[PDB]
RNA sequence: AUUCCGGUUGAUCCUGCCGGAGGCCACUGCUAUGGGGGUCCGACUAAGCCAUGCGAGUCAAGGGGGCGUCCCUUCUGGGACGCCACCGGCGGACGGCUCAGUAACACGUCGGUAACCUACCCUCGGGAGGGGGAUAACCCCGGGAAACUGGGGCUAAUCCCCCAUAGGCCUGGGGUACUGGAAGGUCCCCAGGCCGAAAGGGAGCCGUAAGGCCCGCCCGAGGAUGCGGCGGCGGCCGAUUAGGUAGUUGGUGGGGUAACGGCCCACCAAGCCGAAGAUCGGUACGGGCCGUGAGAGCGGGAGCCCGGAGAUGGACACUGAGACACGGGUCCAGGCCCUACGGGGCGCAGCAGGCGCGAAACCUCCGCAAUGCGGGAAACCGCGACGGGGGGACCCCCAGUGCCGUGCCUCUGGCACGGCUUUUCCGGAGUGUAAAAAGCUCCGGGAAUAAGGGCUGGGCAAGGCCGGUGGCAGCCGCCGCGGUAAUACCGGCGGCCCGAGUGGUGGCCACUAUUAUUGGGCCUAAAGCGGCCGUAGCCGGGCCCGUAAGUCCCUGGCGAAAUCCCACGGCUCAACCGUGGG
């Protein structure tokens, strides 16, 4: 499982959080947010444990975890286990497919890519990713182009016009 | 169970053959022979997996029968056969020679050594005992045996190096282990290491017997006399993880 | 469509080259085995009835296919040795042997 | 990743129960699970029984033939395949299934059989000389509806045997040499006794035949593999079970076993066992792990792997290294079926499928192709073991159910209307089949096109109104709510949650310091024995000294794989699996 459902699940305070982010990162289900929360939670659990124990646990393992965070971009350059603990569940919503294709500005908004990705027109690496919950490396940012294209194989298609209106980039 | 298991399962196949263990449900069980089933490397794995020369067990069985491997100087033909540890496996058809060695990981690796060394097989003998005509005979854990002496004290108690000429099944160039000799460690949890014996002194009574060694780096290890295996003054080279 | 050779093995005992293919299809359907017959004989560089086609799977939407083929010297050897799927996909023989 | 809320009252604080909120696992309602990936399915029932198909064979290159056919040739004549029965050899003890019983040296880990065996197989050494002999096939022939059965003439083989060459085993006496931690196993000589080895190969290749590649046999030794055996420690509940035991504890001799042994036996003794819980009743395959929990702890033994146990209930032997034998036999008990009523045959708690049961669980499918294995030089044969699809609210994971302009409303959005791209869906292409399927995916045509269910008084304040009705009908997990302006009923409308699920019931774990070790108490809330005595047990002032048992440190043997974390990689992606590290 990658579903996290907290001890009190219809509390006021959780519910407010959830409602507000739905075109701020793109939701169409709560689960999608729950995956990201579970990835971060496990990472912070492991980071906490290693720091707790003496130096007699083998440092190789702490080196391998820290490495992965450099690539993913949560600890961009940081190299500190305490630094993992401080992480928000808002730094992993920003590394979503839908908010990193819109960052570059190939997707008009995060909302736009909910039929680009289905219909297979946004490629990363050598392959069409189909998943909003896919998490993108710093490496992976250097190759975001298109494939198997029909509205980008026809500029003359009005699809091309709706997506790019003076070129809407960044994140919102 | 009331009978030898003729089938081995894939989930019963270890990680020491470095095999995918969810592949089917049945793993190749050698017929009883030199060596243990889980401490062996199958002939199926060596042709099929290791080299890509088969993509079905029919390919590999046909390939072995026509001939692509001789183990210890003699012919084989089916893929069922437990290949031992410290053996000599041969590709005559490629001219490769391998040693069957442990890693620090404790998986069986074939470690390449030159065509020259294929001739040699180092024996450190398993026990030494009298047979009729008042001659003592040599033994091994791969069953590899020789007969005929005059009895007596002979070269050692049981910690030997022999040079073995493998097509002839002959023994040559006998040599003791000393307190300045080489051992490679091939059982225990200290495996893959090759060094110089500091001293062979031990705990003099009961079942435990320690032997101790140092290396090139010079780390201090302790292992059983049974898990000390005398290479010689070095014959095969070290195994790498 | 474009066939390129990635990886080449030389198996001496049976006298064959065992070979890996990456085959492309960009904006085009999944590669068509009937043109691939016509294309093969030149790539492998062996006669047309002893240049053998086997294994292809085709990626979902990513336009690259991974695959394997055989180039044989010996017409005698190949039907006997090989596992049945190849022999039908190339067209040589079927399915060997029932109950 | 460590959270609390309603409810004892007029209000208050403490104590304490109940209910609810979380995870997990069955089952049940609606709907759905499109599409795709991995797990899974009489798994808490009757360890009930079965129609029908099926799980066990295989060598003619051991072997002389019978039949069909081939190459021939069309003769003499030798070379092949299928089919067929007899001895050989090997599998059939395995593989597959289930877990009733069993609380124990069942199982796990470490030990350990120098008390014991181990064929096929694998290694090294050596041997296979000579003589003797059969029965199916073939030929002929009787009966039974059957099952099944036959009597005889001939006859092959790695056919079945004897003898010798020896070896094996026992036993008495001498002595050395190998191995050991020791005890002492292995050496050799000698005497007397027994048993008294072996077998070969067709068309090819190697050797002269044997022999060998190949297949198998014999003896000596070893290895591997399987079986049995012993010990340390760990090994459930009820004390409304407290004393138990007569091969029973031991000694001595002996039998029998592969072998130790009160295993069995004779004799001799009266011991053995118990409150650190014996014995008895009761329940339960155990383990790796798993579920839950921040931990401590609690709970569990299911797919799957490991070891043991079983195969209608019970008893019994033979062949084999190995069975007292899961689709073998003998027999008894129960039950079924065929029947000239004389007499036969069985065992799905094996697999499809059936039927009974109940709250609950599948196609009389497809293949031998891949995986494993037995036999075979190989070719290849056998395989409902197995690989897969089918079906299945069984679990998990991934993904789509749109997007833009947009007048105007509830603008983290919605609807009208316009435009665009476009999952299914059609036609085509690969896949794959190892011949289907699973049809997806890709390309061309091409649609905004599968979304539901629960709740709305307080707990969840997350979500509010109308009409009917008026303590009714009903609602309810708890507290409650209805005796006529009802947010609570019922219908309708709206909104909120979650999403191929939602919700209900049952159970388990957290919440529960309501089991207190972490982390609880006993004036009055539940809880001090009416008081003492002293036993078992628990606990001990100061100073020294010996031991280093407890206690701390270090090294080394080891605690199977899988499950778990971290890392990277592959499958669009991920679940998952590989690999390395922990």
Image: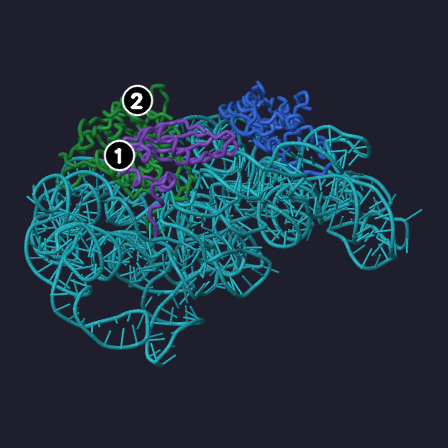
Chain colours: A blue, B green, C purple, D cyan
Of D292 and D18, which appears nearest the observer? D292
Residue position marked by numbered label 2 in the rendering? B196
Residue under the point 55% across and 30% down: A148
Quarter of the figure with the C terminus of chain B: top left
Residue position marked by numbered label 1 in the rendering? B68
Q: Are marks 2 and 1 in contact (CB under 8 Å)?
A: no
Percent x, y of residue D147: 32, 69
- Helix, strand or loop for disc 2: strand
Percent x, y of residue C78: 30, 38
On screen, residue D45 versus residue C38, left or right, reads: right
Q: Are marks 2 and 1 on the same chain?
A: yes
Percent x, y of residue D230: 36, 48
Using a 10 Å C-alpha cutoff, classify the residue at mark 1 as few (fewer than 14 neighbours), some (14 to 19) or many (20 or more).
some
Of A82 and D545, which appears nearest the observer? A82
The answer to whether residue B178 is visible is no
Q: Quadrant of residue A39?
A: top right
Of D261 and B197, which appears nearest the observer? B197
Residue under the point 29% across and 41% down: C80
- Helix, strand or loop for disc 1: loop
Q: Is residue D82 above or below residue D204?
A: below
On screen, residue D235 versus residue D248, left or right, reads: right
Q: Is residue D300 above or below residue D570?
A: below
Name the chain letter of the residue that bears numbered label 2: B
Q: Mark 2 or mark 1, which has the lower sequence index?
A: 1
Name the chain letter of the residue that bears numbered label 1: B
Task: Give the numbered dot on residue B177.
Answer: none
The answer to whether residue B114 is visible is yes
Using a 10 Å C-alpha cutoff, classify the residue at mark 2 as few (fewer than 14 neighbours), some (14 to 19) or many (20 or more).
many
Of D278 and D207, which appears nearest the observer? D207
Percent x, y of residue C6: 40, 26
């Amino acid at each position: 499982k990658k579903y996290e459902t907290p001890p009190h699940p219809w509390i006021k305070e959780r519910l407010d959080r959830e409602r507000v982010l739905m075109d701020k990162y793109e939701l169409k289900n709560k689960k999608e947010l729950w995956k990201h929360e579970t990835q971060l939670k496990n990472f912070r659990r492991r980071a906490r444990r290693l720091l707790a124990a003496r130096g007699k646990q083998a440092e190789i393992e702490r080196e391998q975890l820290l490495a992965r965070l450099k690539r993913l971009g949560l600890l961009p350059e940081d190299a500190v286990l305490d630094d993992v603990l401080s992480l928000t569940i808002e730094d992993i919503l920003e590394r979503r497919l839908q908010t990193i294709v819109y960052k570059k500005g190939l997707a008009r908004t995060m909302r736009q890519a909910r039929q680009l990705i289905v219909h297979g027109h946004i490629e990363v690496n050598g392959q069409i990713i189909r998943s909003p919950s896919y998490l993108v490396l710093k490496e992976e940012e250097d190759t975001i182009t298109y494939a198997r294209t029909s509205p980008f194989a026809n500029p003359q298609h009005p699809e091309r016009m709706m997506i790019e209106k003076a070129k809407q980039g960044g994140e919102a | 169970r009331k009978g030898p298991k003729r089938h081995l399962k894939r989930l019963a196949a270890p990680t020491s053959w470095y095999i995918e263990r969810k592949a089917y449900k049945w793993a190749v069980r050698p017929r009883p022979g030199p060596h243990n089933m889980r401490t062996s490397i199958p002939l199926l794995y060596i042709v099929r997996d290791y080299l890509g020369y088969a993509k079905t067990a029919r390919e590999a069985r046909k390939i072995l029968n026509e001939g692509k491997f001789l183990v210890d100087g003699r012919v084989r033909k089916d893929y069922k056969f437990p290949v031992g540890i410290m053996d000599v496996v041969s590709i005559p058809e490629t001219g490769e020679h391998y040693r069957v060695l442990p890693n620090r990981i404790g998986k069986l690796i074939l470690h390449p050594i030159s065509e020259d060394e294929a001739f040699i097989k180092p024996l450190r003998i398993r026990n030494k005992r009298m047979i009729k005509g008042a001659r003592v005979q040599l033994n091994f854990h791969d069953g590899t045996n020789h007969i005929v002496s005059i009895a007596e004290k002979d070269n050692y108690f049981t910690s030997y190096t022999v040079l073995m000429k493998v097509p002839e099944r002959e023994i040559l160039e006998v040599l003791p282990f000393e307190k300045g000799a080489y051992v490679f460690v091939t059982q225990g949890k200290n495996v893959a290491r090759k060094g110089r014996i500091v001293e062979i002194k031990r705990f003099p009574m009961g079942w435990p017997d320690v032997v101790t060694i140092e290396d090139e780096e010079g780390e201090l290890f302790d292992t059983l006399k049974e898990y000390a295996f005398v290479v010689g003054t070095d014959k095969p080279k070290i195994s790498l993880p | 469509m474009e066939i390129r050779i990635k990886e080449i093995k030389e198996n001496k005992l049976i006298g064959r080259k065992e070979i890996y293919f990456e085959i492309y299809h960009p904006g085009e359907p999944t590669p068509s085995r009937k043109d691939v017959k016509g294309k093969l004989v030149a790539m492998l560089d062996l006669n047309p009835e002893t240049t053998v086609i086997q294994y292809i799977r085709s990626y979902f939407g990513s336009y690259i296919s991974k695959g394997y083929a055989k180039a044989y010297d010996s017409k005698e050897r190949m039907l006997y040795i090989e596992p049945e799927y190849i022999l039908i996909r190339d067209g040589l023989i079927e399915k060997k042997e029932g109950e």
